[PDB]
Image (cartoon, helix red, strand yellow):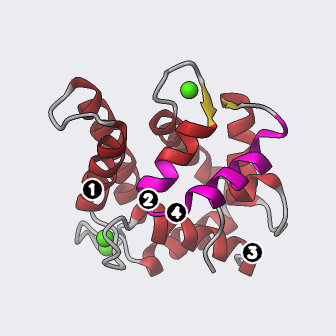
């Protein structure tokens, strides 16, 4: 129902971008930590105005994730619960659209700290470094996304997002939106 190419991409997002604390299970505290880690690299003090926008944005991703995938209502999203959602969307892709669109927008919002509506290499790399990825490797992943440009527009980002979550092609540029892939 889900190709190994897409499984690899789904579990990379789960293990790197959702499970910040590496417990193996996704919980609200992972997204509080994610906001803390990004704010620390940006030099945004906790309780600062900029910090609370970032934390709110991160809590909004968590609640959308919890509503979609926490099937047993324990307040946690297992790796099996994440893959189980995507088996559901494989039968009814049309139902994925509202949530995917909100998640796409949230992820772009967290990266675009200048609010100019494009993601530059320092915006992209800084967020990747906060999630524990290699700087040089994220710099290379950015170069594969930006097609020669200094910035990724919102419009380019929505296309790259669709490829990352939908394409069974192991080598489309959208496969780089969450940096160099983990196996
Ligand atoms: Ca966790
Ligand atoms: Ca659960
Ligand atoms: Ca920007």
Q: Which residues are magenta?
A: 127-148
The residue that mark 3 highlights is 5
Measured in 3D between alpha carbons, the distance from the residue under mark 1 to the one under mark 4, in whole angstroms, is 16 Å
Question: Mark 4 Cα within 10 Å, few/some/many (few <14, many 20+)?
Answer: some
Q: Secondary structure at mark 4?
A: loop
The mark that comes first in sequence, 2 or 1, is: 1
Q: Indicate yes or no whether the magenta region holds residue 143.
A: yes
Q: Position of residue 16 (x, y in %)?
A: 47, 66
From the image, tell me which residue sits under label 1: 33
Q: Observer-nearest residue: 70 or 124?
A: 124
Instruction: Classify mark 1: residues with Cα within 10 Å, few (<14), some (14-19) or many (20+).
Output: some
Question: Alpha-carbon distance for marks 2 and 3?
Answer: 22 Å
Q: Is residue 9 left or right of residue 32?
A: right
- Taking the spot 69% from the left edge, 31% from the top edge, the residue there is 151
Separation (CA) of disc 2 from disc 4? 6 Å
How far from the left and from the top, in percent, is residue 146? 77, 39
Q: Which mark is residue 133?
A: 4
Q: Quadrant of the C terminus?
A: bottom right
Q: Residue at x 84, y 36 (%)?
A: 148
| Comes first in the chain, label 4 or label 3 | 3
> In x, y percent, where is residue 75?
24, 66
């Amino acid at each position: 129902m889900v190709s190994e190419v897409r499984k690899k991409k789904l579990l990379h997002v789960f293990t790197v971008f959702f499970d910040s604390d590496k417990s193996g299970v996704v919980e609200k505290q992972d997204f509080e930590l994610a906001a803390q880690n990004i704010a620390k690299l940006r030099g945004w003090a906790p309780g600062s105005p900029a910090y609370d926008i970032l934390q709110e944005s991160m809590i909004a991703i968590w609640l959308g994730l919890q509503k979609q995938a926490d099937a047993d209502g324990d307040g946690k999203v297992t790796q099996d619960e994440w893959l189980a959602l995507w088996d559901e969307y494989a039968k009814d892709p049309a139902a994925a659209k509202d949530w995917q669109n909100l998640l796409c927008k949230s992820i772009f919002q967290i990266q675009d700290s200048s609010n100019d509506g494009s993601v530059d290499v320092n915006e992209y790399v800084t967020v990747h470094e906060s999630f524990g990825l290699n700087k040089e490797e994220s710099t290379e992943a950015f170069k594969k996304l930006a097609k020669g440009k200094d910035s990724i527009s919102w419009a380019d980002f929505q296309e790259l997002w669709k490829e990352y979550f939908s394409s069974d092609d192991p080598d489309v540029p959208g496969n780089y939106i969450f940096g160099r892939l983990t196996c």
